[PDB]
Amino acid sequence: FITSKIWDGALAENNHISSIGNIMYTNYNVWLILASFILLLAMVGAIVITIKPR
Amino acid sequence: TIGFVYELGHDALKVHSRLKSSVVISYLGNI
Ligand SMILES: CCCCCCCCCCCCO[C@@H]1O[C@H](CO)[C@@H](O[C@H]2O[C@H](CO)[C@@H](O)[C@H](O)[C@H]2O)[C@H](O)[C@H]1O
Image (cartoon, rainbow over all chains, first blue to last red; front, top):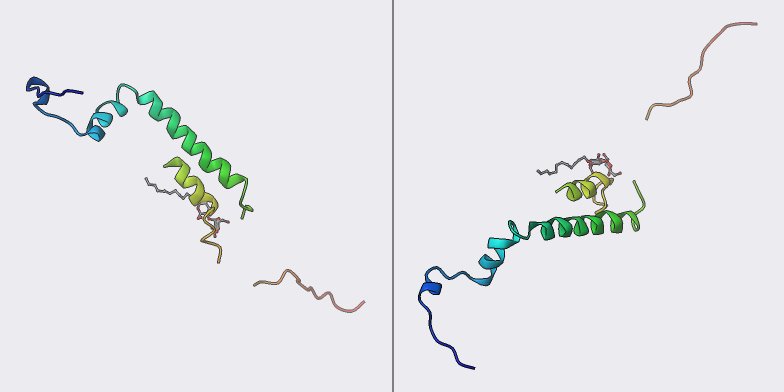
């Protein structure tokens, strides 16, 4: 495999987490909504099937 | 956060949760 440098594409390079962040909360934010609800269901459901209330 | 107030509201962590007498007599007197 061969690689070479680029200058226009290296102006302000971002780490992978900043690149994930640039799109995780804006363009693909519906995926964040569903995931927020899956985690929220795993909270309510697992608490309700294990603990004795009060 | 709302799911966090649910376990706060229910003590799921089971961290929390760690007298006047009902018998009242009245005197009426002789028969
Ligand atoms: C933006 C940040 C917001 C942070 C959270 C904001 C406050 C929301 C959380 C509290 C909401 C009220 O939730 C309340 O929690 C208390 C404390 O466990 C519970 O407390 C009551 O039940 C529990 C469980 O039997 C008992 O241990 C406790 O002695 C009793 O007082 C109430 O049943 C619940 O109504």
